[PDB]
Image (spheres, coloured by chain):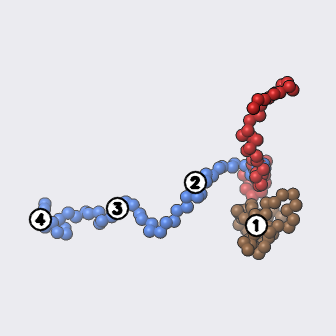
Chain colours: A brown, B red, C blue
Amino acid sequence: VAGLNDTHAARKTGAFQFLCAHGGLAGGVVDKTKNGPADPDTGAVTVKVAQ
Amino acid sequence: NPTLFVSYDQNGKKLSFANWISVLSPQDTPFVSMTGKESINQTIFSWQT
Amino acid sequence: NPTLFVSYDQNGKKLSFANWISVLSPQDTPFVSMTGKESINQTIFSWQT
């Protein structure tokens, strides 16, 4: 699984959104609602559709 | 011995780790840290008004 | 030999050129230039929160 020197996506880096929430990782943060599944312990719900 | 320079050429990496922990939610309380505490050895304290 | 002082008296002019280029639209990004970058040699990084 180590060969294929050419058949490989170049690279990618975790950006601001992936570091902040990375809600679903759908090839670009899709901002429909993604408020938060449960966040039981604390808050940190800094993702909203801006109603 | 540089042979592949893909995954296993340089083993013993740092795993993309840094020596600093990030608490995403602010949980500091500067109030008490500002208000300095004073020591009392005995237990017969008394103050005046 | 000053003879005409119109067009060809002083040849070898600077063509009204200056040594400074003017980018009419602002295209600078002080954000990254302010946020300093740090070097990492290994690839086993780790940070703490």
- What amino acid is labelled 3 in the image? Ala
Q: CA distance from mark 4 to mark 1?
A: 79 Å
Q: Position of residue C27 (x, y in %)?
A: 51, 65
**Nearest-to-viewer mark from 4 and 1:** 1
Front in this rendered view, residue C41 or A18: A18
Residue indicated by mark 2 = C34
- What amino acid is labelled 4 in the image? Thr
In the picture, residue A23 is in which quadrant? bottom right
Q: Earlier in the sequence, mark 2 or mark 4?
A: 4
Q: CA distance from mark 3 to mark 4?
A: 28 Å
Do marks 2 and 1 both belong to one polypeptide chain? no
Residue at coordinates 29% horizontally, 66% vertically from top-left?
C15
Residue indicated by mark 4 = C3
Which secondary structure, mark 3? loop
- What amino acid is labelled 2 in the image? Met
Q: Earlier in the sequence, mark 3 or mark 2?
A: 3
Furthest residue to the left? Answer: C3
**Nearest-to-viewer mark from 3 and 4:** 3
Q: CA distance from mark 2 to mark 1?
A: 27 Å
Q: CA distance from mark 2 to mark 4?
A: 58 Å
Q: Which mark is residue A47?
A: 1
Residue at coordinates 49% horizontally, 66% vertically from top-left?
C26
Instruction: Report the side of C7 relative to A31 (left or right).
Output: left
From where the camera sits, is residue C23 visible? yes
Label 4 crowding class (10 Å Cα cut-off): few <14, some 14-19, many 20+?
few
Q: Chain of mark 2?
A: C
Q: Say if mark 4 contacts mark 1, CB within 8 Å.
A: no
Which secondary structure, mark 1? loop
Do marks 2 and 4 both belong to one polypeptide chain? yes
Residue indicated by mark 3 = C18
